Length: 44
Ligand SMILES: [Zn+2]
Image (cartoon, rainbow, N blue to C red; front, side, top):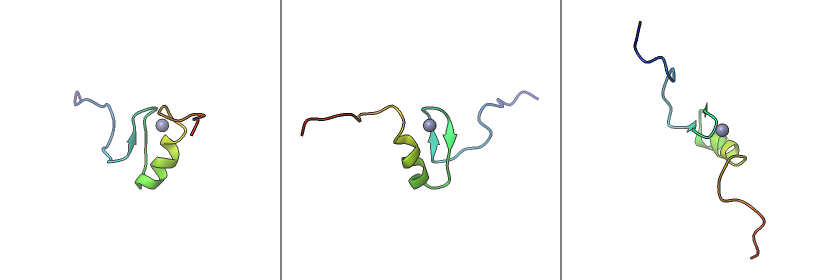
């Protein structure tokens, strides 16, 4: 059976950073928060 068994299932919220899917964006946001991205000690 060769049908690309990479990524069983598809969802609108799939953290590419590590590779974790969620149910509601909300839950994802809290996850992506601790992931690569523009966030640090700014000046203001
Ligand atoms: Zn992640």
